[PDB]
Every structure is written in C-alpha cells, then in structure tokens.
Amino acid sequence: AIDFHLSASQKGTYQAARSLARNLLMPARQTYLQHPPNSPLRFQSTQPTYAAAVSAGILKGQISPAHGGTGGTLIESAILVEECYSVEPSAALTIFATGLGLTPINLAAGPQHAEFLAPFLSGEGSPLASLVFSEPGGVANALEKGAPGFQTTARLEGDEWVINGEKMWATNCAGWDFKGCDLACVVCRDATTPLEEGQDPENKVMIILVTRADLDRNGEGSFEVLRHVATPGHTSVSGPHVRYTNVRVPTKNVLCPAGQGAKVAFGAFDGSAVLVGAMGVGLMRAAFDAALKFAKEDNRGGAVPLLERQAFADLLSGVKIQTEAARALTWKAAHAMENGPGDYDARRELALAAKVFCSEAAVKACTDVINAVGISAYDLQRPFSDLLNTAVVLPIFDGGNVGIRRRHLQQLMLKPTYDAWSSTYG
Amino acid sequence: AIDFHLSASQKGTYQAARSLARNLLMPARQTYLQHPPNSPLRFQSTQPTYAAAVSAGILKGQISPAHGGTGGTLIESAILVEECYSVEPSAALTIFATGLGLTPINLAAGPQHAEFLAPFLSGEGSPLASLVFSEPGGVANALEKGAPGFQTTARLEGDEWVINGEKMWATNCAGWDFKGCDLACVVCRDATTPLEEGQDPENKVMIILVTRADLDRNGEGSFEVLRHVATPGHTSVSGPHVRYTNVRVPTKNVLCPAGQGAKVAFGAFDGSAVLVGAMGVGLMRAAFDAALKFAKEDNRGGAVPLLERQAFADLLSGVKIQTEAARALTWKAAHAMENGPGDYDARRELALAAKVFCSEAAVKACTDVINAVGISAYDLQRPFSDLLNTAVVLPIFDGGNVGIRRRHLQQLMLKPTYDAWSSTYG
Amino acid sequence: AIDFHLSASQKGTYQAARSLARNLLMPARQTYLQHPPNSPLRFQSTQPTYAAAVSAGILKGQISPAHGGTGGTLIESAILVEECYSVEPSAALTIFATGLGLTPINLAAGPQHAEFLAPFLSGEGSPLASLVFSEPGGVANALEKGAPGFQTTARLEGDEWVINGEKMWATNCAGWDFKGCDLACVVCRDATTPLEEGQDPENKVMIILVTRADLDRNGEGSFEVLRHVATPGHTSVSGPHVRYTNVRVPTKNVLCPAGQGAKVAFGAFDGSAVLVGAMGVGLMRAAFDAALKFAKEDNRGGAVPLLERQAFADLLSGVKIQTEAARALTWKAAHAMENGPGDYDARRELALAAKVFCSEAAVKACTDVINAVGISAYDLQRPFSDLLNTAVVLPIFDGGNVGIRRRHLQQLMLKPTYDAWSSTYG
Amino acid sequence: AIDFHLSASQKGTYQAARSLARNLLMPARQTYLQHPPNSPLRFQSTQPTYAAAVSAGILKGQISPAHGGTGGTLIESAILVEECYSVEPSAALTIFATGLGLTPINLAAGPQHAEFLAPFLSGEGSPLASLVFSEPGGVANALEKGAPGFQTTARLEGDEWVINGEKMWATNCAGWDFKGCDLACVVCRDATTPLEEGQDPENKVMIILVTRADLDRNGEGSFEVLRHVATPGHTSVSGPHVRYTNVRVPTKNVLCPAGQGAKVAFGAFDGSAVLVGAMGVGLMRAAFDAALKFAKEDNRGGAVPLLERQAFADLLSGVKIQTEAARALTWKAAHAMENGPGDYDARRELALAAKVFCSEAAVKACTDVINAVGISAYDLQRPFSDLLNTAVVLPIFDGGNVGIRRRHLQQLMLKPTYDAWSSTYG
Ligand SMILES: Cc1cc2nc3c(=O)[nH]c(=O)nc-3n(C[C@H](O)[C@H](O)[C@H](O)COP(=O)(O)OP(=O)(O)OC[C@H]3O[C@@H](n4cnc5c(N)ncnc54)[C@H](O)[C@@H]3O)c2cc1C
Ligand SMILES: Cc1cc2nc3c(=O)[nH]c(=O)nc-3n(C[C@H](O)[C@H](O)[C@H](O)COP(=O)(O)OP(=O)(O)OC[C@H]3O[C@@H](n4cnc5c(N)ncnc54)[C@H](O)[C@@H]3O)c2cc1C
Ligand SMILES: Cc1cc2nc3c(=O)[nH]c(=O)nc-3n(C[C@H](O)[C@H](O)[C@H](O)COP(=O)(O)OP(=O)(O)OC[C@H]3O[C@@H](n4cnc5c(N)ncnc54)[C@H](O)[C@@H]3O)c2cc1C
Ligand SMILES: Cc1cc2nc3c(=O)[nH]c(=O)nc-3n(C[C@H](O)[C@H](O)[C@H](O)COP(=O)(O)OP(=O)(O)OC[C@H]3O[C@@H](n4cnc5c(N)ncnc54)[C@H](O)[C@@H]3O)c2cc1C
Ligand SMILES: [Mg+2]
Ligand SMILES: [Mg+2]
C-alpha cells in the first residue's frame, strides 16, 4: 500500500548515514584540503577515513547475503547516498565506487568467485574495488556495429586469459598506491576469435576479474598510470587514465563469458542510476539549505528580510519543489527495482528516469541558488561553487544522459512488450 | 515503510475510476460536443451524465464518513482524478467542483449543518455544490493589508445575514438552470462593523452557506448571471460572472464566523492543490499515450520507425520522465497531507509543490508532444490541441501559481518554525 | 556600417504595414467571426480584405523585379509580417501564403513562365497562389533513402505531364470557390522512370505549376476537396486535404525538372524561415502589449499596482527581453540571406536559427503571459488563448524544427567547409 | 538603413582585437598559471602584460574624445570585448575594469578633473582605475527607503571630505601592490547631515575620487586589504574586501555631489551592461568552438562522426542559435544606446536586456556543451569547466540579474512614459 513513512529500520539507516557523514566524511574533507586541488595526494589522504568506513561494516553491506554479505536495499542505499552527498560528495564517492565495483559480482558471481570477495567480507583493512568500463577514446559506441569496439581486449592463450588495454575514469582502479586496486571488474572484448561479418559486437563482451595479486604476479609494467586527471569537483576521487599490459589471469578469473558481459555491466549501471538520482537529491538539499541559511541571516542591506523579495523567494521555492519531486521519483525507482510492479524493462525505465531527472535538476538547482544568493556565491569561502562543480558530473558520468541513458530509454519504448504505466498500475 | 504497491482498495479505486471515465464521462463528451463550443448549453447538457454518477455514489464519496458519506483518502482521490483527467477533463471537473464545494463543510461543519448535506447524501437527483471564492476583480490580494479586500460582503441585520457582491469563475455556482446551485459556500468579508485601523483583514473573512432554497425565498433578482465566460478548454464547465443582491439568510447558514473563513477556505485549497497535481499527471499520461500511439503507427513516411530518431524519442522519454516525477510527488503530497510526518505547515508545502510542479509540467508536456508529433498535431481530429488547452488552466486556476501558490510557499519559508525536510525525515 | 535604424523607405514599409493591419486586417477579423470556426466559409468572408491588399500592390511586391514585380527585401517583409501577426495572424497568412507559392517562381522561373504571373501582376481582383508540398503521410522523410517518397506523383506521357496525388496543409490551394486556386506550385515525384537501386531519391523531385485554367480544362474529378482540416489557430485560413486526379499539363508547366525541385523547395523554405521568425516576433509583441495593458489598468484588487509585484514584472520583462532578441536575430538573418557575408550555407544557418529561436520563444512567451495575467487569460473575450494557439503552430509548420530544420543544421555543420562565424565576421 | 555589415573601421577593430587577445592575453594566462589557483600573485603577475596593453593604446580607448581620449562606439567596444572573452576572460576583465572605473569620469568630469585622467592618457606605465561601488553587506538595496543605505560614508569637515567604509568586489581597487589603485571612483553616502524623515536616500549619494597619492598622503592605516577573495574563475582578477579609514580629500576630488552620484553610477552600469552582453557572446563562441573542435576530431569510438549523432548535433546547434541571438541583441543595444531611437529610458531597457539575456544564455551554453562533450568535459585539461566557472559570474556581477537588473526593468515598465517599442520603431 502507498506509504512514504520510513520504517524503524529505514530511520536507523538515515541516522547512521547522518553520523557517517558528520563523523567520517567531514574530517576527511578537512584532511584532503591540506593538499592542492590537483594533487593525487587528496585521494591518498582519505584512506584512513575509508578504513573507518570499512570497520563500520560499509563494504559488507555492499555484498549480497547470497554471497555472504550483509547487503541492504536500494531504498536504504538511496537514503545513505543523499545524506552523504548533502555533506561531502568526494570522499563518499570513493566508498560508493567500491560498491559499484562489487555490483557485477553480486549480479553474476558463482560459488567459484567466493575467494575474490574475501578481503571485502573481512570487516577490516581498506580494500578497493572498481568497475573498469570506460576508456580514453570513449565507450558510448562500444556495442555499435561497424565501430572499433572496446579497445581493451582479452585473449585465451593456453589456460590463461590475457588482457591488454587502456582504461580511464574507472574510480578506484589504481588502488591506494597507484599500482592497482584489490579487485577490478574489467569490461573487455574477447578477441580470441575475430568478430564475424555482421555479428553483433555485444556477442564478444566479457567481464574478467583482475586482483592486485594478479598484477603483482604478472610483474613490472603490467599496470601503469598514464595520467592522473584533475577534476573541478570530486577532487579526492581517483579514476586515472591507466594501461594493462599482457595481464595473464587463470580461467577462474572470468566473471562473465563472452556475450554476457554487456548485460551485467548495464545491470550494474541500472542500480547506480538510482543512486545517481540520490546524489542529485543530496546536492539539491545542500544547495537549498545553504541558500535558505544565507537568506535567514543576511538581508543584503534591505529594509526587509531577503525572503520577502518575491524574485528571491521564487528561486528558492522552485529548488525546493524540484528536490521534493526528485526524491519521490528516486524512491519510486529504488522501490520498483527490487519490488515491481512491471518486468525488468519497466523497472529499469524508472531507474533511468531518476538518473536523468535528478542529475539535471541538481545542475539547474545549483545555478538557480547562485543567482538567488548573488555575487556572494562567487566567493569560494561559501559552498555554492563546489556544489555546482559537483553537480555537473551527474548528467555525464555513470553513463552520460545524452549518449547512453537516453539511447536506452529509446530502445525500451521500441519494444513490442513496452507497457507505459506497468511500473505503477501493475 | 516505503512502499509504492497499490493496496486492494487502491486497485479498486483505480478500476472504478477507469469504469466511471469510460462509461459516464466519455458519453458526456459525445453529448456536449453536439452543442456550440462557446455555449452554456454544453454544461447544461451534462446533467444526465452527472445524475448517473450521483446514482453510482460519486457525491456520497465526496463526503467524509464523519458526516454520513463514504469519503476515502486523498491518495485514492489522486488516483481517481488522474484517470478521469486522462480521459475527459471537462465533464470530470464539474463533478470534482461539487467535491470542492463540499470540502469546507467536511472541514468545519457543525451539528446544524447536517441538513445542508442531505441532498448530497441522497444518492439521487443531480445536486450541484460550489466553493464560491473568486471575484471579477481578482482575489490574490483579498487578505492584503491596505487593499480593498473581498468585494463580496455580508452584514448582520437583526437575525439574518445579508449578502452582497459579485463572484466569477466559481464552478457550478449558477446551477443547471443558471438561477442558483443547490449549495454554495460563499466566502466573503464581514462588514457589520468596519475593519479597524491596521487590523488584519483575515479577521473579517467568513464562509456563509447559500442554498437554492434561500435564493428562491429571496425572490426576483436576488441572483443573476451577468456573463457566461467561454473558455478554450473545460467547455462544459460553468463558472459565470454572477451577482448576489441582498441575499438574506438565517444565522444557521454561517459555516465560518468572521475570522475563521480564510483558514478553512485555504485548507480546502490545500487538498485541491494535491488533486490539481493529479489532474496534471492525467493530462501528461494522456499526451504521452496519444504520442506513443501515433509513433507506433506512423513512421512519417520514413526509412526507419519514428522512435528511431534520437530527436523524436528524446521528446517522448522527456515527457515520460516528467510524468513519473509528477505522480511520485503528487502521491507523496497526498500521503503526507493525511499522515505526515511534519507540522501542517510542513505537509502543506508539499501539496503546494505538487500543484505548481505538475500544473506547469503538464503544459510543457503538451507543448513537447505537439512538437514531436509535428504538423499533424495542429489537426483538430487529434487530441493534442484540446490537451494543451486543458493543461493551460492548471497553473492559473485553483489559486494561480504566480500570485497565490508561490506567495504561500514564500510565507511558509519565512516562518521561524520552517523546517525544510521534516515532511520527509521528521 | 552596423545600423539598426530604418531607412526612410523602411519607415514607409512599416507605416504601410500598420495601415494595412489596422484598416484591412482588423475588420477582416470582425467579419469572419460571423461564421463557424471549423467552417471554410469563415475563410470566404476574407475576400474583400485580400482584394484590398491586392489593390494596394501587395501581390506585385511578392514578385521580383526580374519577373516584372515590385519585389522588396526580406527585411521589409519581416517588418510587414511582424506588424500583421501582432494584429491578425489568420487573415494575414492567406496573403503571405500566396507569397510563398510565388517564391519558387522567383527562384526558378525562366522566360517561358511569364504567362503564369500575369494574374498576379495585373493588380486586379484576388488571385491566390500556393506552394503545394505537404501530404497526409508527412514529408520530413520523402527525401530519405528507403522510404515510399512523395505520394503525389507526376509522369511524362508523350508531351504532357500527368499528375496524381493527395495533398494537405497547402494554404490557399483550393481557391475561393473550392474548385482550385489560380496558381499552385505542386512539389512531386517523377514516376516516369522508376528510381534506380541505391539512388538518392532527391533526383526524382520536381515542381510543376497547375493553374485553375488547367483544372477547368481537365474537367470534373480532376480536383477534389476530400477533407477540410480544422485548426486551433489561423481559423480563417483554408488548406484542406485535396486530391489531384489525372491532372494533365503541357511541358511548359514544369518549373523544376526532376532533380532540381528539392533545392528550390528548401530555398523557398529558407526565405520563409526568416518570416516565421517575424511571425514569432509579432505574436510576442502582441502578447507583451496585452499583458502590459492589462497590468496598467487592473491591479487585481491589490494595494499596489500589478507591476510592483516582482514575480509579475519579471514574467513581463522576460518576454520583452526574448522579443528584442527574436527581432534582432530575425533582422540579422533577413539581412544576411540577401547580403552575406556568409556563403549560402552560412546564410541559411541564420535563417533556420531565426525560425527555431523565434517560434519556440513565441510559444514560451504566450505561456508566460498567461501565467502572469492569471485566470483572466482563460477568458476567450481576452486575446491570450488565441495568441498561444497561433504560436504553437510556428515550430511545426513550414518545416518543423525537430524533423527538418535541425536536421539541416546538422548537415550544415557536418560540411568540411562549415565556417561558424563567417556570417558575421567574414 | 538596417545593415549588419561591419564598416572598414569595425573590421579594423575586430582584427586588432584578435591580435591583442592572441599577443597580450594568451601570454598573461601562461604567466599567471605558474602561481597557485587562489594566489593574489596571479593578479600581480599580469602587470607586465597590462603595461603592454597600455602601450598599445587600450586605456586611451577607454576615455571619451571629450576628455582627450580616443574612445569609440559601444559597438566597437562590444567587438573587442567578445573577442577578448572568447580567448582569455580573466586577464581581459582586469583591463576592462579600468574602463569601468573611468566611466563615471567620462560621464561627469568637470574642468578640475582633467589632472586625474592624465596618467591614463600617457600611453605608458600601468595605471589602474576602479569603480568602487560594491560592499560586503550587499548593495542591491542601497537606495531603498527604510534601509541602512551604503555603509561607506563621506562627511565634509572644513575644506576636506572624509571617507570611511568597507568595500568588496571592486575590481582593481587595491592596485598592483595592494595599497590602493591609481584612481578609484568611490560611491558613498553623504553623512554630513542626516537623512530627513521620509527623504529619498538617493539624495545623499555621491561619487568621490580617491587617488593613490591621496592614500599615501593620508598615511598608514588609511587603506587596508582585509581579505583576498578566491573565485572559481577570473583567478587573476583582484576585487578584495578592503577598508578606507578617515581618508581625507580636497573638494576638487568630488565628482558627483550628493544627490547626483546614483544617476552617474547607474549610467556607468548601463554602458557596462552592453559589454556584459558581449562577454556572454564571447564565452558562448568559445564554448561552441571548443565543442565543435572536439566533435570534428573525436567520434567517441563510433561508426560515424560525432556530429552525426542527432543528440550531439542538436545540443551544438542550440548553442549556435542562442549565440547568434545574443550577439544580435548585444549589437542592437550597443547601437540604440548611442543612436536611439527612443528616450534614454527606452535605450536603457535594451542595455539591461542584453546583459540579462546574454549572461544567462552563456551559463546555459556552457552546461549544454558539457553534456554534449560528455565525461571528457570534467577533465581540467580541457577548457569546458573553466568556461562554465567564468560564465556563472555574468548573471551575478555588474549588478546581479535578480536583485538589480530586473528591478530596473520593473521600474522602467512602471513609468507612465514607458513606450514599449520606441527603441525600435520610435
Ligand atoms: C567522478 C567520475 C567517476 C566515474 N566512475 C566510473 C567508474 O566507476 N567506472 C567506469 O568505468 N567509468 C566511470 N566514470 C566514467 C563515466 O561513467 C562516463 O559516463 C563514461 O566514461 C561514459 O562517458 P560518456 O557518457 O560521455 O560517453 P562518451 O563515449 O565519452 O560520449 C561522450 C558524448 O558523446 C556523445 N555521443 C557519443 N555517442 C553517442 C551516440 N551514440 N548517440 C548520441 N550521442 C553520442 C554524447 O553527447 C556523449 O555525451 C567516472 C567518471 C567520473 C568523472
Ligand atoms: C475552469 C475553472 C474553474 C474554477 N473553479 C473555481 C471554483 O470552483 N471556485 C472559485 O472560487 N474559483 C474558481 N476558479 C478560479 C480560480 O480558482 C483562480 O485561480 C482564482 O480566481 C485566482 O486567480 P489568480 O490566481 O489568477 O488570481 P488573480 O487575483 O486573478 O491574479 C492574477 C495574476 O495577477 C498577478 N498577481 C496578483 N497579485 C499578485 C501578488 N500579490 N504577487 C504576485 N503576483 C500577483 C499574478 O501573476 C496572478 O497570476 C476557476 C477558474 C476556472 C477557469
Ligand atoms: C498554418 C499552416 C500552413 C501551412 N502552409 C503550407 C504550405 O503553404 N505548403 C506546404 O507544402 N505545407 C504547408 N504547411 C505544412 C508545413 O509545411 C509542415 O511543416 C510540413 O508538412 C512538414 O511538417 P513536419 O515538420 O511536422 O514534418 P512531418 O514529416 O509531418 O513530421 C512531423 C514530426 O515527425 C518527426 N520526424 C520525422 N522525421 C524525422 C527525422 N528524420 N528526424 C527527427 N524527427 C523526425 C519530427 O519530430 C517532426 O516534428 C502548413 C501547415 C500549417 C499548420
Ligand atoms: C569578478 C567580479 C568583478 C566585479 N567588478 C566590480 C567592480 O568593478 N566594481 C564594483 O563595485 N563591484 C564589482 N563586482 C561586484 C558586482 O558588481 C556585483 O554584481 C554587485 O556587488 C551586486 O551584487 P548583487 O547583484 O548580488 O547584489 P546583492 O546586494 O549582493 O544581492 C544579492 C542577492 O540578493 C537578492 N536580492 C537582494 N535585494 C533584492 C531585491 N531588492 N529584490 C530581489 N532580490 C534581491 C538577489 O537575488 C541578489 O542576487 C564584481 C564582482 C566580481 C565577482
Ligand atoms: Mg479592480
Ligand atoms: Mg548586513
């Protein structure tokens, strides 16, 4: 039955989220601010915060009970993500990115993959996982007929899969010391045999695990950071341009065989679309809160309070309205992904809707709040610039809206089985 | 606990709504279409349909069980309103307006007001009710200090209240024969004693009941239609410019005494704000459905299916995303209004949000699908033009966004007790 | 030398436009309102107006001096169109549609075509022209490799061309008495010899003249009015669904040989794009004027003038700003089309820009003004609803923004010779 | 005569602007980039290239011919500003800000003021001027009845004016060495006698010159930089929070006596509004060019060029359209400000319009281009982030759109003399 009240457990999640952001993430921010904005040392300095998160069981919660994890719901994740993004986006993302890295494992792992999950179930240390998908040259057209396909390839040679390629933007993939993370899910193209004339490129896509142990065993030059990328927000996040060279792994490392990889990757990106929605809600909440606090304490030298000016008030209420719509849609999507109604195609349309709606609304909200607050918002002592520069990544990352998210919505509607309102009216 | 599944009762509401719309409303439209677009004969011709709806208990459903009715939840009203607006907005509104007319009684009735509700609990005939608020000269500033205030006044003379003034836009107020509807809740300004220097005009606002009976007793010309207004949509809806001249009623007709009328009127308007949200969702659904249908069956003489144009698909998926957000927000507001969490001030901000967001989103969606369908959509054989001309009213009526709904949002934020997210997180 | 001042002549053009609109167009409106909105005899009552326009040399002005006319500049046309659309769009469009019909003749006519312009150069009566290009099944994809192409076809049987096809939306094509207009440029597909395998469907496109004399000559059944298309705006304009059956004409009637018709059609559409911009400017001007007028006389019962409300004033000034941008862009495109400094590609990018910017701005302006004016704008006694219903056609007619106008912009930019700012800086 | 062709003198200005930007501004950028992002040394490091611009005659060009300068038309200024902003906004703004500082003197100088202008007319050194208006507490309400008014005050004590107050954001006011620029136009309120009951605060507003020589004469503590403000773009621009303490100047230093200052300051801001339009155009051009460059050399791993994606193309053409409207509007305002037709009030409206339209269109263009380019736009190696962070200042600076520019538009429309289209057709 239609209910917007948090359960006692969901309220616990909210309170826990508040404490995590306040006690772990805020100190992480003061810590990385001690290094210049283009320094990879920002990322490295967050390792002790990450460890503290690990000790509190965050990584265990990112693994499904099927695999021995404690795993929660997308709804609970959405609540956590909103709160963290309202406080400290960059340090939070490093943690959420490990969750993304572990998602393909939740979706496709079998019993033989348990050994790979062990470091993450330990409840100690600071292991990092990464979903290693994107490439320097772009991947919006990795599955397009007539195109080159993924640049990163795997070849079965004897009893070993051999990986070669360059990747970029894959959060966490280089690990704390830039020599490779604990567990990478590398999305690549099987090239043991050539793509046949007219064959669907998706038939060749795999996901193969690569651990830090694999890289070490393969020795010098097997993994290399080609370029650290400085970004205008998320300054403690590390997703460098990297290269894998002749990285040989055992057959047990294959997660998704050729022809099953794309589906699992997009499956992982469906879940994260929901949390990108939550990211947007969190930034919008932070923007509204900061603008409202500005108004309530600063009348800009006027004869009346700032909120008594219709033009200012209407900008703020506009943001509040979009934020409330964004959270409702995000929760609807989080609920539907795990409960229906509607088949998977219908559930996924909502996750994509949340992603697209909230990411763009977050950018618009940030720009509106800047105009409302006025010239003061150009002062970097105030939070407004960082908010905007955090928001603008939402539409373009986790599968950009223009080149990926919207192309999928197109394919969904094209299907004969498309049933517009099934995700609502059963 | 966060849940978006419809209960059995909510599924039932939805099924009954589909039935009502297809079986009663659609025929009402075939009937009124036979009269000229700008003729009050359209409204008059809907009486048979209306009475049939009365026979199915629709009016009983607009009255709270506390007063003898079968009224349900705001959530169920949202589901009903969405479906009716997706099929036939004009015939639907005349019915919903009686519901609005009855709301102030549902909210503030005393034991002595039971007799006034009798015709509406009868289950037969075709009694009309009206919330009579708007006036030819505007009402956004009715409560504004230094302004004239309501043009409609009532003054206590002996043992009868005497009502004088002109109203406009008040749906149903003139009844089927244009000589006065069964039950009108007349909002007006006590003028028995003058507003005192600097006194809050809200102190004088009353709601007085006026029945067809009262009007008949008052004789020749106590009620007069001064002008029938022709509208581009809602053509079977009747809310003329009218005048009450020396309408004398017994003290039992007072629903809200001077200084209590404003709060009750605005309380009614908070509930209706949620349902305007639902109206917006329903038009959006109708526009998306019609556009999708067209696209599935006309490739515009193209070499591929219409949906295969990035540009066309993007307009439609844009509408879908906005509609899902609009419904999610509407249901959240519907739920919160009756369940919290948060102050009434908190709950209220969400109802206003739904009104503003969905009304404007409805107009955008209709504009978008017109562009997507193309030149064909100027063709009055298709539903698109009437969709737009219906949607355009949503932002301006039931308290316009610009001068009323946003002014209320402004005032809520201005309160020292404003607590932004209490309506979600407590 | 950059100059926005009207020359003496251009001021003359503007005064003439003002006079035409005030003395001819306004009365045409009061006149055609006497007849039904979906009736084609509303259209017939506008003849005296058209004939007065003809008397004043308007039609001679639509023909270039090369072909014996008194043709002016695109800038003067933009001035005229803006004024007319700010007053009376429907009656005005009948006149302008003749200008469009005549345009391919201005672009493509040779010595042998002089005979066809005679009725338009005589300064007598009320001859109508029409560019008959649009078909029931759409035409955005008539030029596309794989599609059924134009459904209207012409084939060379001996020494006469035989034309068969159905048409729609072609303003003016059926004449005053509905038996066919004086002069139609029929755009069609050469079905004399089948299109070759893998051949650009453009190669078979023609334009062929068809006079009322030709229709009369082919006798009964040669021209038939199938369906009259009712539209929400332009209610006095007649552009029905018609069929040409075995319409036989001499080889002199060919204006554009197979393979040349597409370029000339789009050439004509470039010119009109600029004028669609002017239409948009005109509607925006009227919307702003009406809203401003409303505000200066009606304070909506407020304690202060309506323009003292920030939210209201910002809506109005937003419209004023867009209108000024719209006109400045329209004039730039009008100037560049005939004067450079672009090459033809650069020039038409600006014409398309004007069409897209102003059409969309007009729709947005009409929506904004309705919200600003409020509930009063739903009253058909006021001009706001009609304004919206006219503007909504601008993005979709004369080559919709979505399936053609932007498709051409894309092709322009794809050319290796594209030089972004050459239309301004050389 | 409506003409969009540049004259030989305007072509000359364009060519000189290209050369100046490339030779002076680009090297300024490579120079200041050697210092940290937030360092005041970025500003200081631009002195040598500022001196080169001075030697090139740039400051002479900011002074009106009436004072011995070679200042040209606003149109030519708009051409220069667009080019400079398309190349290097930050170093450009420092130069343009000296022009703003000289503007009140161009507008109001008396014979006694020629000595103050002398340093700026020599063609050597690197003199800086500042219009010192803005204050930490805000200034949108400096003229509001019932408000505190400017915090910066001046009092006549004998034969000297004594100035006290804090200013913030006033570009260049602190000079190269942070101890005060060469020539500051300080906007302040006369506090010699108190404001009378219900008196217009405008009556007390003055502009008083303050030179570095004045500051040195007044001794230690008379001028102090309180805080250098770090900004997300314009990182070489210095407009710190500063304090003037008991700064005494002779009466010759008074530029606008009490009651004349506000009109001159706003006069300066009317001219600057046009040039902000041009800054907007320049950033839009730069964003469009950078995205087109990326598209023409990077197909994102596709089977077709990036421009063949309808999605990408539609985003770029949208930016191109807005840019053409922006420039057209800016040039119209430039021309009308100096040539009419219309009142000063009418001309003024167009300047305000260009500022509001173009500033907001620049922000929208930058966000659109980021979405089109995709994740690559988040890489600080590419120009898109810096473009956005430059663009967001435009709506909020030089008199913010929400608090100032739109309030001026509102006051214009409120005048009985308002004549909507006089600046076009008057
Ligand atoms: C902070 C951060 C964290 C990230 N996390 C990860 C991660 O954990 N793992 C990972 O693998 N990657 C990660 N990424 C990368 C991110 O997911 C990107 O969205 C991904 O690289 C795809 O980028 P894109 O959508 O721009 O596609 P691209 O291929 O780069 O396309 C770019 C643009 O080209 C256009 N385009 C291309 N093809 C088409 C088409 N067919 N139709 C229409 N338009 C088209 C679109 O306009 C699109 O916006 C991260 C990036 C950042 C900045
Ligand atoms: C189909 C239909 C059904 C209706 N049903 C009913 C009904 O059942 N009962 C009833 O009483 N009425 C009814 N109405 C009227 C409807 O409720 C209107 O919204 C109501 O009259 C208020 O209109 P408004 O908001 O435009 O206020 P107005 O006072 O008309 O204000 C108009 C505009 O002025 C501007 N404005 C005025 N004051 C301010 C301010 N202080 N600040 C900023 N801007 C301001 C705003 O832009 C506002 O939009 C109906 C109307 C229609 C068309
Ligand atoms: C008042 C009025 C006057 C008119 N006057 C004339 C006239 O004088 N002469 C004449 O010939 N016609 C006339 N027309 C019709 C006008 O020329 C139409 O614009 C023309 O028929 C093309 O319509 P369209 O752009 O909707 O294209 P259509 O082919 O009808 O398609 C419409 C929609 O299909 C989608 N679409 C189709 N293909 C694509 C694609 N490849 N990419 C993206 N989207 C696509 C687009 O979203 C587009 O909006 C008139 C119409 C009106 C209303
Ligand atoms: C790079 C840069 C260069 C600059 N150059 C100069 C310079 O050379 N000289 C100089 O003096 N300053 C300069 N400034 C400051 C600039 O001119 C600002 O626009 C100015 O300080 C006014 O800011 P504001 O419009 O936000 O007004 P504020 O008073 O700061 O108002 C802030 C916000 O409050 C709200 N508000 C306040 N009052 C009202 C109201 N009455 N109605 C509605 N809303 C209201 C509005 O949303 C407004 O945006 C510069 C600033 C920067 C960043
Ligand atoms: Mg009045
Ligand atoms: Mg203060």
Image (spheres, coloured by chain):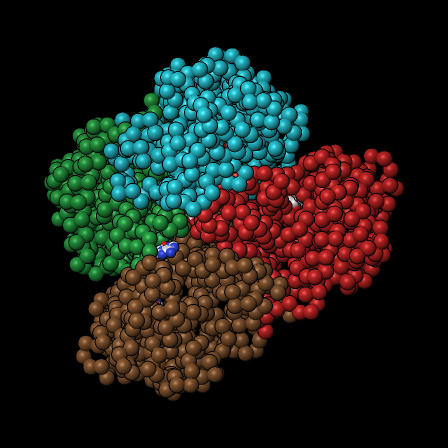
Chain colours: A cyan, B green, C brown, D red
> In which quadrant will I find the C terminus of chain A?
top left
Could you tell me which residue is drawn at 83 percent across and 44 percent down? D212
**Residue A337 in the image, given as x and y percentages of width and height:** 34, 29
Residue beneath the point at 62% across and 53% down: D282
Q: Nearer the viewer, residue C387 or D394?
A: D394
| Horizontal side of residue C93 vs D172, given as left or right | left
Count of labels shown? 0
Observer-nearest of A104 and C120: A104
The percent coordinates of residue D100 (x first, y second) are: 71, 52
Instruction: Report whether residue C216 is seen.
Output: yes
Residue C192 or residue A125, whichever sits in front: C192
**Going by the image, does A160 lie left or right of D1?**
left
Q: Position of residue A285 (x, y in %)?
A: 49, 31
* Above-or-below relation of D277 to C149: above
Quadrant location of residue A13?
top left
Q: Quadrant of residue A347?
A: top left
The answer to whether any part of residue D362 appears in the image is: no
Quarter holding the N terminus of chain A? top left
Q: Quadrant of residue A244?
A: top right
User: For the view shown, which residue lies furthest in the right direction?
Assistant: D217
- Which residue lies at the image location 53% right of the left edge and 72% below the top edge? C338
* Residue toward you, D163 or C233: C233
Q: Position of residue D8 (x, y in %)?
A: 69, 69
Q: Which residue is rendered at x = 33% and y = 82% of the image?
A: C251
* Farthest residue, direction front: A158
Check the image and report above or below for A319 versus D295: above
Would you place residue D154 above or below residue C288 in this image?
above
Residue B418 is left or right of residue B278, and the answer is right
